[PDB]
Image (tube, rainbow, N blue to C red):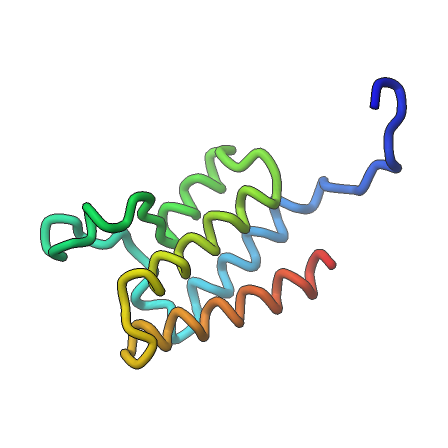
Length: 115
């Protein structure tokens, strides 16, 4: 509350560490469905169904331009990429399996880096 604060967690490395995680996601072999925005002209149904499209390149631009106020907003966009993927793709498809794998990969890096 006013003049009553928990001890200050060091957040000065968060930007660099989120960049490193994102590099590792970008370079994973199953990253291909997620690297670029879904082409809303060429993929029927995507525009209407997925209210908030997200992809790694868009996260990279937002990161590089100070559009994440803190590490939680960064994790919310990463998770959005995988939540979108599950919304649009069957579990038993290459892209559906890609999303589950990437989410797992992300969550481990996240826990090991910050928890």
